Image (cartoon, coloured by chain):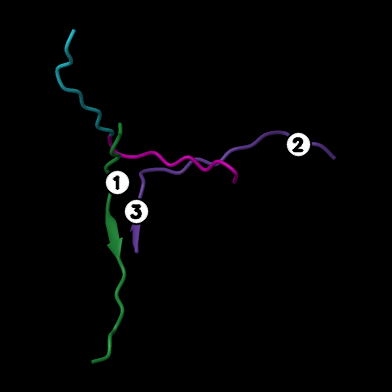
Chain colours: A purple, B green, C cyan
Amino acid sequence: TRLSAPVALAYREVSTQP
Amino acid sequence: VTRLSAPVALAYREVSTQP
Amino acid sequence: KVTRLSAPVALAYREVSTQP
């Protein structure tokens, strides 16, 4: 019943394969 | 047992309630 | 995705005096 707010949000990820 | 992590803001919800 | 990080404003540890 609460939500919070961060300063920044960091997703990821790399070269992936056919 | 170790950390706390103070955020920026904090948001609260609200429900209308009947008597 | 699997691991979205988030980065807070500040942390806070603590510790008392500990005996020998």
Residue placed under numbered mark 2 in the picture: A16
Q: Are marks 3 and 2 on the same chain?
A: yes
Where are the magenta residues, as a range? C1-10
**Percent coordinates x, y for residue B18 in the rendering:** 27, 90
Q: Between residues B3 and B5, which one lies in front from this camera angle?
A: B3
Secondary element at tag 2: loop
Quarter of the image for residue B2 reads top left
In the rendered image, residue A4, in percent from the top left (x then y), is placed at 34, 53
**The magenta stretch spans residue A16:** no
Which amino acid does the dot numbered 1 rest on?
A: Pro
Alpha-carbon neighbours of circle 1 within 10 Å: few (<14), some, or many (≥20)?
some
Please tell me how crowded label 3 is: few (under 14), some (14-19), or many (20+) other residues with Cα within 10 Å: few
For the point 28% across and 56% down, the residue is B10
Instruction: State if disc 1 and disc 2 touch (CB < 8 Å).
Output: no
Numbered label attached to residue B7: 1
Left or right: B16 in relation to C19: right
Instruction: Give the distance between the C-alpha atoms of the residues marked 2 and 1, in whole angstroms.
Output: 34 Å
Residue drawn at x 18%, y 15% is C18
| SS of the residue under disc 3 | strand
Residue name at image x 21 percent, y 27 percent: C14
> Taken as a whole, is the magenta stretch helix, strand or loop?
loop
Q: Which residue is mark 3?
A: A4
Say above or below: C15 vs B14: above
In the image as oriented, which residue stretches furthest toward the left? C17
- Measured from the top left, where is residue A14 in percent x and y? 67, 34
